[PDB]
Image: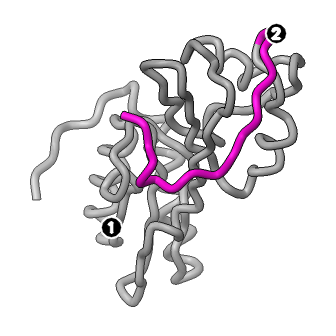
Amino acid sequence: GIYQHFSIEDRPFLDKGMEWIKKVEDSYAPFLTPFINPHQEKLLKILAKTYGLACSSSGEFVSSEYVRVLLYPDYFQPEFSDFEISLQEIVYSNKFEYLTHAKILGTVINQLGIERKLFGDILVDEERAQIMINQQFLLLFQDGLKKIGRIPVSLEERPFTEKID
Protein backbone atom coordinates (compact mmCIF):
# COMPACT_ATOMS: atom_id res chain seq x y z
CA GLY A 1 0.00 0.00 0.00
CA ILE A 2 0.86 3.68 0.03
CA TYR A 3 1.64 5.39 3.33
CA GLN A 4 2.55 8.83 4.41
CA HIS A 5 6.15 9.91 3.84
CA PHE A 6 8.50 9.68 6.77
CA SER A 7 10.35 12.71 8.05
CA ILE A 8 13.90 13.32 9.26
CA GLU A 9 12.44 13.56 12.80
CA ASP A 10 11.24 9.93 12.44
CA ARG A 11 14.67 8.40 11.76
CA PRO A 12 15.79 7.58 15.31
CA PHE A 13 12.53 5.73 16.02
CA LEU A 14 12.53 4.04 12.62
CA ASP A 15 16.05 2.83 13.32
CA LYS A 16 14.79 1.17 16.55
CA GLY A 17 11.78 -0.18 14.66
CA MET A 18 14.04 -1.90 12.14
CA GLU A 19 15.96 -3.53 15.02
CA TRP A 20 12.71 -4.89 16.41
CA ILE A 21 11.65 -6.22 13.01
CA LYS A 22 15.06 -7.94 12.66
CA LYS A 23 14.57 -9.59 16.09
CA VAL A 24 11.36 -11.14 14.82
CA GLU A 25 13.04 -12.20 11.58
CA ASP A 26 15.88 -13.77 13.59
CA SER A 27 13.76 -15.56 16.13
CA TYR A 28 10.53 -16.30 14.19
CA ALA A 29 8.91 -15.34 17.49
CA PRO A 30 6.85 -12.39 18.71
CA PHE A 31 8.62 -9.27 19.93
CA LEU A 32 6.88 -6.94 22.41
CA THR A 33 7.90 -3.28 22.35
CA PRO A 34 8.12 -0.84 25.21
CA PHE A 35 5.48 1.81 25.60
CA ILE A 36 5.40 4.12 22.54
CA ASN A 37 3.37 7.17 21.56
CA PRO A 38 0.60 7.28 18.91
CA HIS A 39 2.89 8.67 16.22
CA GLN A 40 5.44 5.94 16.92
CA GLU A 41 2.68 3.33 16.78
CA LYS A 42 1.72 4.58 13.33
CA LEU A 43 5.38 4.42 12.15
CA LEU A 44 5.87 0.90 13.40
CA LYS A 45 2.59 -0.27 11.76
CA ILE A 46 3.92 1.08 8.42
CA LEU A 47 7.32 -0.66 8.83
CA ALA A 48 5.63 -3.94 9.85
CA LYS A 49 3.37 -3.89 6.75
CA THR A 50 6.39 -3.13 4.56
CA TYR A 51 8.24 -6.22 5.86
CA GLY A 52 5.18 -7.76 6.03
CA LEU A 53 5.14 -8.89 9.64
CA ALA A 54 1.85 -8.96 11.54
CA CYS A 55 1.48 -6.18 14.09
CA SER A 56 -1.08 -5.73 16.96
CA SER A 57 -1.22 -2.68 19.23
CA SER A 58 -2.47 -2.77 22.83
CA GLY A 59 -4.58 0.24 21.71
CA GLU A 60 -6.68 -2.12 19.63
CA PHE A 61 -7.71 -3.90 22.93
CA VAL A 62 -7.67 -1.05 25.51
CA SER A 63 -7.98 2.47 24.21
CA SER A 64 -5.02 4.48 25.25
CA GLU A 65 -2.56 7.04 24.14
CA TYR A 66 0.65 5.17 25.00
CA VAL A 67 0.67 1.62 23.70
CA ARG A 68 2.78 -1.47 23.43
CA VAL A 69 3.04 -3.31 20.16
CA LEU A 70 3.50 -6.91 19.34
CA LEU A 71 5.36 -7.87 16.14
CA TYR A 72 4.92 -11.56 15.15
CA PRO A 73 4.97 -14.36 12.58
CA ASP A 74 1.61 -15.62 11.23
CA TYR A 75 1.27 -18.69 13.40
CA PHE A 76 0.74 -16.37 16.45
CA GLN A 77 -1.91 -16.14 18.39
CA PRO A 78 -2.18 -12.66 20.18
CA GLU A 79 -4.24 -12.20 23.37
CA PHE A 80 -4.29 -9.09 25.58
CA SER A 81 -2.10 -10.85 28.14
CA ASP A 82 0.73 -11.03 25.50
CA PHE A 83 1.16 -7.21 25.92
CA GLU A 84 2.24 -7.67 29.57
CA ILE A 85 0.31 -4.56 30.75
CA SER A 86 -1.06 -4.20 34.30
CA LEU A 87 -3.58 -1.56 35.38
CA GLN A 88 -2.74 -0.17 38.83
CA GLU A 89 -5.12 1.88 40.90
CA ILE A 90 -3.31 4.55 42.89
CA VAL A 91 -5.27 4.09 46.11
CA TYR A 92 -5.47 7.48 47.75
CA SER A 93 -5.57 10.01 44.91
CA ASN A 94 -2.83 12.03 43.42
CA LYS A 95 -4.62 14.35 42.88
CA PHE A 96 -2.75 15.64 39.72
CA GLU A 97 -1.64 13.78 36.53
CA TYR A 98 1.39 16.13 36.67
CA LEU A 99 2.22 15.29 40.26
CA THR A 100 1.93 11.50 39.66
CA HIS A 101 4.05 11.69 36.53
CA ALA A 102 6.69 13.72 38.31
CA LYS A 103 6.96 11.26 41.17
CA ILE A 104 7.30 8.38 38.76
CA LEU A 105 10.14 9.84 36.63
CA GLY A 106 12.22 10.77 39.75
CA THR A 107 12.16 11.21 42.87
CA VAL A 108 13.61 9.96 45.30
CA ILE A 109 10.38 10.71 47.42
CA ASN A 110 9.27 7.89 47.19
CA GLN A 111 12.09 6.48 45.01
CA LEU A 112 11.55 6.08 41.25
CA GLY A 113 13.84 7.07 38.45
CA ILE A 114 11.45 5.19 36.18
CA GLU A 115 11.87 5.66 32.39
CA ARG A 116 8.79 6.74 30.40
CA LYS A 117 9.05 3.58 28.27
CA LEU A 118 8.15 1.29 31.27
CA PHE A 119 4.64 2.73 31.68
CA GLY A 120 1.88 4.17 29.58
CA ASP A 121 -1.03 6.37 30.45
CA ILE A 122 -1.66 7.93 33.80
CA LEU A 123 -5.41 8.41 34.17
CA VAL A 124 -7.29 10.89 36.38
CA ASP A 125 -10.02 13.53 35.88
CA GLU A 126 -11.11 13.44 39.38
CA GLU A 127 -9.71 12.06 42.65
CA ARG A 128 -9.26 8.42 41.57
CA ALA A 129 -6.06 7.74 39.69
CA GLN A 130 -4.58 4.85 37.80
CA ILE A 131 -1.46 3.94 35.86
CA MET A 132 -0.88 1.38 33.06
CA ILE A 133 2.51 -0.33 33.58
CA ASN A 134 4.80 -2.94 32.07
CA GLN A 135 3.92 -5.88 34.38
CA GLN A 136 7.54 -7.03 34.40
CA PHE A 137 8.12 -3.97 36.65
CA LEU A 138 5.10 -4.56 38.99
CA LEU A 139 7.29 -4.70 42.12
CA LEU A 140 9.24 -1.63 41.16
CA PHE A 141 5.90 0.26 41.13
CA GLN A 142 4.01 -1.43 43.92
CA ASP A 143 6.95 -1.31 46.36
CA GLY A 144 8.47 1.98 45.16
CA LEU A 145 5.41 4.22 44.65
CA LYS A 146 4.33 4.66 48.28
CA LYS A 147 3.90 8.47 48.46
CA ILE A 148 3.35 11.29 46.11
CA GLY A 149 4.32 14.68 47.49
CA ARG A 150 3.28 14.29 51.09
CA ILE A 151 0.31 11.98 50.66
CA PRO A 152 0.75 8.22 51.03
CA VAL A 153 -0.46 5.98 48.18
CA SER A 154 -0.88 2.23 47.57
CA LEU A 155 -0.93 0.61 44.12
CA GLU A 156 -3.41 -2.25 43.53
CA GLU A 157 -4.24 -4.38 40.44
CA ARG A 158 -7.57 -3.50 38.72
CA PRO A 159 -9.22 -5.08 35.60
CA PHE A 160 -9.15 -2.96 32.45
CA THR A 161 -12.96 -3.22 32.73
CA GLU A 162 -12.51 -0.89 35.72
CA LYS A 163 -10.40 1.50 33.72
CA ILE A 164 -10.77 5.27 34.03
CA ASP A 165 -11.62 7.44 31.01
Where is residue 146, by image quadrant? top right
Which portion, as a residue range, is magenta?
Answer: 149-165
Whichever of labels 1 and 2 marks the residue nearer the N terminus, that label is 1
Left or right of 72 in this view: 97? right
Give the tally of numbered discs.
2
Q: Is residue 11 left or right of residue 111?
A: left
Mark in the foreground, 1 or 2:
2
Q: Which residue shows up at 20% across the image and 37% down it?
A: 5
Sort mark 2 into few (<14), some (14-19) or many (20+) by Cα contacts within 10 Å: few
Q: Provide the residue designation for mark 1.
A: 51
Could you tell me residue 134's position as x and y percent?
64, 51
The circle on residue 150 is: 2
In the image shown, does 17 or 111 lie closer to the viewer? 111
Specify the quadrant of the image occupied by residue 79: bottom left
User: Which part of the image, by quadrant, shows the C terminus?
Assistant: top left
Residue 90: name its quadrant.
top right
Q: Residue at x 37, y 52 (%)?
A: 62
- Describe the element under mark 2 as helix, strand or loop: loop
Instruction: Based on the picture, tell me whether residue 41 belongs to the magenta stretch.
Output: no
Are the residues tagged 1 and 2 within 8 Å (C-beta)?
Answer: no
- The outermost residue toward the left is 2
Height in image: 84 above or below 25?
Answer: above
Task: Return the residue nearer the eye: 84 or 14.
Answer: 84
The picture places residue 78, in percent across and down from the top left corner, at 42, 76
Image quadrant containing the N terminus: bottom left
